[PDB]
Length: 323
Ligand SMILES: *Cc1[nH]c(Cc2[nH]c(Cc3[nH]c(Cc4[nH]cc(CCC(=O)O)c4CC(=O)O)c(CCC(=O)O)c3CC(=O)O)c(CCC(=O)O)c2CC(=O)O)c(CCC(=O)O)c1CC(=O)O
Image (cartoon, rainbow, N blue to C red):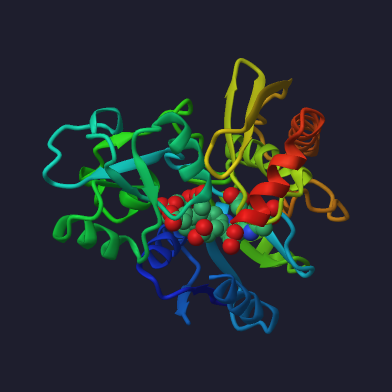
């Protein structure tokens, strides 16, 4: 009867879970949804819950899900993407500044290798430094202490907190391309639970799905391991899917970046697809035509092979061993 939704207890995970449950209740007003509250450790804890039929589905930020999931789990819904951009919050003394106009040697807080690599390259006169804590803690550090002049974070995190007004600068791709999956939510479920897969398949957004298949296929084929600097940009326009991807050394000084495109129509109709169909980069979308999904996957693989031909494996190897 009731659909059990497991969640981490942190505030942003609860907000994300609530928003997905709200969309499910809009399609299914006659159904009961119960929220059960209980990093890579907690991902496995939620997977255990799901393996043991303690919960039926779990909501993650998509960028937080590896491109290979354990067997028995799949991503049963890619929700419509929120804003994928990275953003800057400034120290309060910096009224109306941007990263371009901060004094030289200002310290910017980020614990993302990806952001730090791209931003050191774009802003060589700033210092980029690790900062610890959840979003409320980083904002306190910034408001109360003098170490940091600014911090970097995902716009969609602040947006979900109701704190969009804290944003002082939205970074564009030439400054900082986003992480694979950033801004999309993914729902993880048991790989062979057909009732729940049909249920959450109403959440799939076809454009976001194809974009993220391509972003994820690209990342998987690079085989860089976790936490190397890799970033993407995707757009669907005029029948084309565009994928830009890049890799960087930790200090940003070495980089390879290329763009490929493919003719991929965004499907507007749901279709009743076959059940034997294997998942693509951990995603199961049986109600969306399969052809465009495979084409999005092939685009990511292609762009990854191009980058590897131009030397990406050596950049990723060095970055991985120096993190
Ligand atoms: C091998 C491998 N492991 C993973 C899982 C994985 N993903 C990341 C990316 C990551 N996560 C966070 C924290 C965060 N998650 C969501 C938000 C809000 C935005 C949103 O919903 O999209 C946030 C906060 C925020 O971004 O503001 C971060 C940022 C950490 C920080 O700011 O200090 C990042 C890094 C980034 O965006 O560049 C991680 C890293 C976690 C970390 O660095 O703290 C991990 C696990 C790990 O590497 O240990 C993946 C998937 C990565 C992807 O798809 O983007 C992979 C890749 C693979 O399978 O090859």
